[PDB]
Image (cartoon, helix red, strand yellow):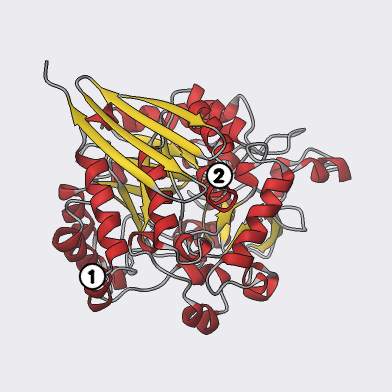
Amino acid sequence: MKIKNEVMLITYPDSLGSNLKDLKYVLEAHLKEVVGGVHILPFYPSSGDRGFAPMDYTKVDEPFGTWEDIREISNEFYTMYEFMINHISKESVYFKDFIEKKEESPYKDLFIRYSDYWPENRPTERDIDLIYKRKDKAPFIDVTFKDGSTDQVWCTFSEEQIDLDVRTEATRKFVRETLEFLAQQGASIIRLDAFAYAIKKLDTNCFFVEPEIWELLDWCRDILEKHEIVLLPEIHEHYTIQEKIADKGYPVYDFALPMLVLHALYSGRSERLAHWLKACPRKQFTTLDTHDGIGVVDVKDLLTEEEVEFTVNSLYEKGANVKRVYSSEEYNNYQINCTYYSALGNDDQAYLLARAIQMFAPGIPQVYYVGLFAGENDIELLEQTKEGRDINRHYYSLEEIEKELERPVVQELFDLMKFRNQSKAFDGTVDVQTTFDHLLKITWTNGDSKAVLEANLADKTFKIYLEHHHH
């Protein structure tokens, strides 16, 4: 199914019932009106980071179901699957073949060896300090080959995740074939996880390295264009990097909206949110919640330092069942572990207003499954796992879902989503206005049709208006 200008669900393969068969039942039985698309988070066999250390793209991890189950969901909903362009599991056949056969491995060129990458008398202390690091150490792990020789391989994230070398014909063949395989399982979008990390180059920070990153993105886009599949480069960065990707014609994520909407609702102010809604790229995937925590670095310069501090303290002070310790190292964590609904104090009025803003914001709205069901902080699972992120990764039963559908806030959110999916106005052009300091008007116009949101951020009341003029 081709991408449409309709809400996309974000879910785990096993978070809505048990597996992909349950996911398909929940979509067809409850969600046909309210989502046109589904982002299934990585469902390949993985050796860590719940899907983000994949071993093999050519199979569905057996507990979730099969590729056939994914294909049936693709027939009714436009689908987004993940490709990890930056790295693959140490538990992959590809890496295990490299450790065994070394120079005789057909997969040796998929990985970046320290001995091969650094010229003589390098790296210097400066070389290592220049690298944008996500941990305290240089981004390398030791390996021992079968033949007893030793080296280091580039490793950006966890020791489960070995970086691919996108400079080599071997990596290009792996990526090309995987993108072709994913194209053939019905994807309308491919999300490129951590794509900004994929370029390693001497005398650079190895982060969003120009011009090579444009070569890499265009090369992938070229492979998918022939199937009318969209490439979605995923980055959590300053909004100027989103603007630069959008300039090269790609869709981007709006990871700024979540904190801009929290700040607007806590402060009762429309100014910062109206600025972003006017200036943001028109081709984007908007978010309040994702599978991850609420991102604060993403809203840098779109709120002042004091506005960010006020918003983070409002979340902890007004949030429903949220503690500072849940986003500390005690729970394995700048991102805040909190459901969006619990971030607004489980306030139905403020939450619906947040979702109405999201529906009217430039882009395709993405609705994380926990937010779909106005999910509150899962303290039970958080304590069971000690994963801070789990506060916002509740596992719903089919029975639990049937009960969530009876909440007025959930029924009201479904009506909002159906309206955003059905109303021609959203396929037109958008006009943003503010009156005084607390009011926000968003008008979509498409020919004889106009859709309007009038929101008072101070009293959290709002009006939705649709008209068809026939003259």
Mark 1 residue crowding within 10 angstroms, few (<14) / some (14–19) / many (20+): few
Residue at image position (68%, 76%) is 330
- Measured as percent of width and height from the top left, residue 259 is found at 56, 49
Q: Is 391 on the left-hand or right-hand side of 158?
A: left
For the question of whether residue 177 can be seen, the reply is: no
Residue at image position (65%, 41%) is 303
Q: Is 36 on the left-hand or right-hand side of 103?
A: left
Which image quarter: residue 201? top right
- Measured as percent of width and height from the top left, residue 3 is found at 26, 37
Quadrant showing the N terminus: top left
| Closer to us: 284 or 421 | 421
Check whether the beta carbons of the residues at disc 2 and disc 1 lie within 8 A of each other: no
Residue at image position (54%, 83%) is 383
Badge 1 marks a residue whose secondary structure is: loop
* Amino acid type indicated by mark 2: Leu
Which numbered disc, 2 or 1, marks the residue that appears first in the sequence? 2
Q: Is residue 88 above or below residue 359?
A: below
Q: Residue furthest left?
A: 470
Q: CA distance from mark 2 to mark 1?
A: 30 Å
Mark 2 residue crowding within 10 angstroms, few (<14) / some (14–19) / many (20+): many
* Amino acid type indicated by mark 1: Glu
| Closer to us: 239 or 224 | 239
Badge 2 marks a residue whose secondary structure is: helix
Quadrant showing the C terminus: top left
Q: Which residue is mark 1?
A: 406
Q: Is residue 315 above or below residue 466?
A: below
Q: Which residue is mark 2?
A: 260
- Measured as percent of width and height from the top left, residue 70 is found at 23, 56
Q: Is residue 39 above or below residue 204?
A: below
- Measured as percent of width and height from the top left, residue 148 is found at 68, 65
